Amino acid sequence: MPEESSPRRTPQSIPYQDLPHLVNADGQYLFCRYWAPTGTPKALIFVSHGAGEHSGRYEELARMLMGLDLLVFAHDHVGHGQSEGERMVVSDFHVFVRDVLQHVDSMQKDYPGLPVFLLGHSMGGAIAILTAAERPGHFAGMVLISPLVLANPESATTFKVLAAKVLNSVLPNLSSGPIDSSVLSRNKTEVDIYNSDPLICRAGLKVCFGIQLLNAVSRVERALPKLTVPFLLLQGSADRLCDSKGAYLLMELAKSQDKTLKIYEGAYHVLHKELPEVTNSVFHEINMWVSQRTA
Ligand SMILES: O=C1CO[C@@H]2CCN(C(=O)N3CCC(Cc4ccc(C(F)(F)F)cc4)CC3)C[C@H]2N1
Ligand code: NA
Ligand code: NA
């Protein structure tokens, strides 16, 4: 008699049968998270995390959103957190978009007739933009926290040179240096928390992944005249990872009739984990913006 093979486990050795999950189009398990209110939800909202991190870092934001009667849902992108895949590797950037759409489609089957919002930070913001641009008119709104629209000019040069070296030769292990944690936030405790989380990948960015981030930036630029979804864009003026010029470009080139930008003077990249004055404002602004569009 044939027997079933050992249960599929996360990269941290936890069986997926003991966790909320989804199998993507490539047969890879994605770890999922849900924060549902006690009553009938007013709307659904997918949270899209950034490069190297994972969905567990959105606990406080998600609880605030759930407190507004929204059903919040997320998954760790392939190659991240508790999902399967080689760490920080993606065959094509569109895999992330495809997987967000599968999860949104699955949730809309269980909760039909509800409006659906997107919330994305950094690389997750580029994913949210590309997701909304692929389905014009489908999403009720998008909340972008320091989205990857334009990379820091020095880093864009570094990866364009590295991409040209691997495009011309075979160098599978080539990587840049790691993301300097000190530029993430002026809140030193949040920098320390980022440096202590075992689910965060703090290795140098592989050049193949850098190529997909260059693809994301190029695709976001081409998508902006197709973008009509309502959005709230939050950006720090001293962001060394996602250049603030990208936020101004998004405000200018998107076709959206409902677009708002809030600049946080002197703030770094991770606005929802910045100094308390900034973080409290970020939570308040997202609460007001989503409340106004779910009433
Ligand atoms: O809470 C956190 C923890 O710290 C995280 C660092 C990486 N973040 C990102 O998603 N990125 C995206 C990639 C950026 C670096 C980069 C590299 C290459 C390119 C390009 F030139 F190749 F396109 C673009 C940006 C840094 C910010 C998300 C951040 N959020
Ligand atoms: Na399949
Ligand atoms: Na419903």
Image (cartoon, grey):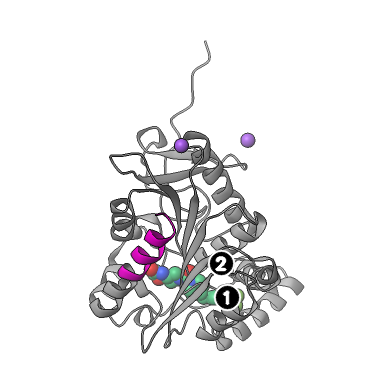
Q: Amino acid at mark 1?
A: Val
Task: Locate residue 276 relative to residue 142 in the image: left or right.
Answer: left
Query: Residue at point 62% right, 65% down?
Result: 228
Task: Identify the residue position indicated by label 1 in the image.
Answer: 149
42 in relation to 18, above or below:
below
Where on the picture, by quarter, is residue 200? bottom left
For the residues labelled 1 and 2, the Cα–Cα distance comes to 7 Å
Query: Of the numbered discs in the image, which one, if any, rests on residue 126?
Result: 2
Q: Main secondary structure of the magenta part?
A: helix
The answer to whether any part of residue 204 appears in the image is no
Is residue 25 found inside the magenta-colored segment of the image? no
Q: Amino acid at mark 2?
A: Ala
64 in relation to 160, above or below:
above
Task: Locate residue 233 relative to residue 39 in the image: left or right.
Answer: right
Q: Nearer the viewer, residue 108 or 267?
A: 108
Mark 2 beta carbon near ligand 1 (under 8 Å): yes
